[PDB]
Image (tube, rainbow, N blue to C red):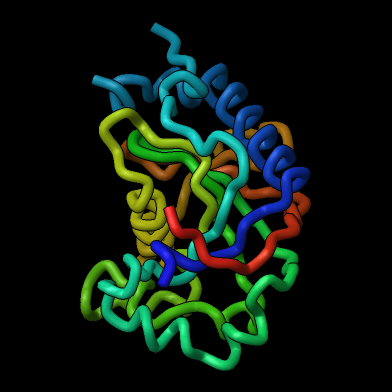
Length: 209
């Protein structure tokens, strides 16, 4: 079994989203709202492209099931599904509706279709036992991580953002960047909601390390 399954972006789609991410970081770091919050981000204008120093080098992806070569619970069962066999090596179009920044990670929020959710595993959309976020809420594409941060944190950061909003504490609109509206979520967290959702082409496959 692979390390994980997921949707792996084409070269062109990866480059498009990477560039969108970079422009977001560049503009956010120069935005007055961000500058006001600098000590809530890093306890001196900060170059966020540099801050998020660990980045995917080329092909970007949206993970479905972490398998750990069969050691992750449910990996084998997931791999054996007819729907996976029918989807393997097939091209999909994923919708990105927002970009986000926290002190740990930056990435893209993916909003999966009903069909794509057939490939989404159980028990990944919770931060606590009693959480009731929509199926697929964790779906994301990592665009960068702070130096001491593991890439898995990107999904956890998105879940935290979505939990905050579901709980009734939504972001404050503080302005407009390229591609959409900027929201301050507090505690170093920022979200760009895209005026036009970005569509990326990607192949469902397994990654072996």
